[PDB]
Length: 227
Length: 227
Image 1 (spheres, each protein chain N blue to C red):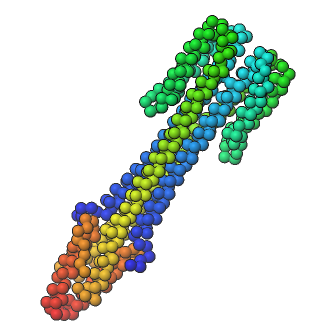
Image 2 (tube, one colour; image 1 turned 45 degrees about the horizontal axis):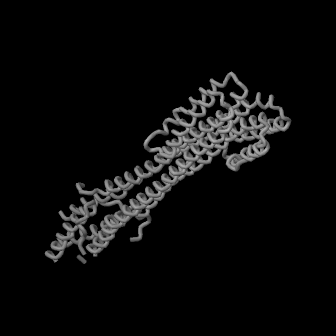
Image 3 (tube, rainbow over the protein chains, first blue to last red; image 1 turned 120 degrees about the vertical axis):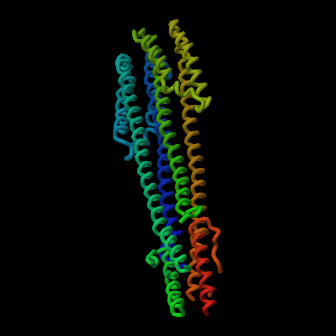
């Protein structure tokens, strides 16, 4: 039973790599789906920022006692963990620069609020809101890019899987099914004309080819030496 | 070569079902990721609605000539395809009812705007914005639910795959490797003591067991009938 490449070991290896590719494909898609929820929440907070931008305008105009609390809440939203987490190597620059520039433009907005410059603030709010919109767009573009990459990756994994399958089946035909058909004939021959058999297979059929030939060899001498 | 269950056919079937499960798992995750982009865009538009709610307040207060254009844009955003597409059997009621109620509450808001009731509109805007926030929350909850279902589904597919693998390998051991070891001994026996071999296998080893026995049977009579 000691063969160099037992058939079970070779199939188990194939299944291992096939299953590994499956888990990798599905795993990457699921991780990307989780990341999608975080992107959604970034988009949610950005929309909170747009609403809060107009509300500050109303606060100043009406002299609301909540002005300063609201200015503070705005600063906090701007620094939400979900937005600061975008500042990482694998997130595109389009997203991170636009995030940086939202912080920079807020500085001028807040300063103008501090100076009770309602005319300026009212004349510039559309602009700031537009900047938030472009930040959101960059986020949506990043999201779509990730999806398309996951599709590309799944297609590749697909090729690896189909290739692994095709090759293993081809190997089973060549290293298992073929020699079995030859053993069948080379057995119904000896039952009724003493083709030899491929002993160079590194699996169980190579061992059977040997021991068969060994047997089939001495029967040629025992059936001819006596007959 | 005519056997009822050739080994290649049984492996190809196993691979078929394994690959099918892989594609189903990864496919469902990718479809869910695509749906995630649509959810994100629903969240984006909902945030547009919050900003636009305060802006209408400023329009009325300042007597902006854009009031009516903005009222119109609000109505349009509210009826975006991305939001109306939520009205479907597979989207939860939590999402669809909240969407319905945003439309209903907008009716009263727009009516109060038409009556130049700035005091009411200013005293109720926080409420409406809150309703939009709860709609967003329902969307985020739907998103998380989908992800968790896709995780559950991928785990199940995992069990199907590992089960298919384990069974096929077990079958290869029982219906291929075992009879080969018996053919090996039952061949080094006849080379040097004439155990018989399992002809009831429905694969190629069952045919080889037969023809072997057929052969090994007549050699018992030809080696004893002459000796």
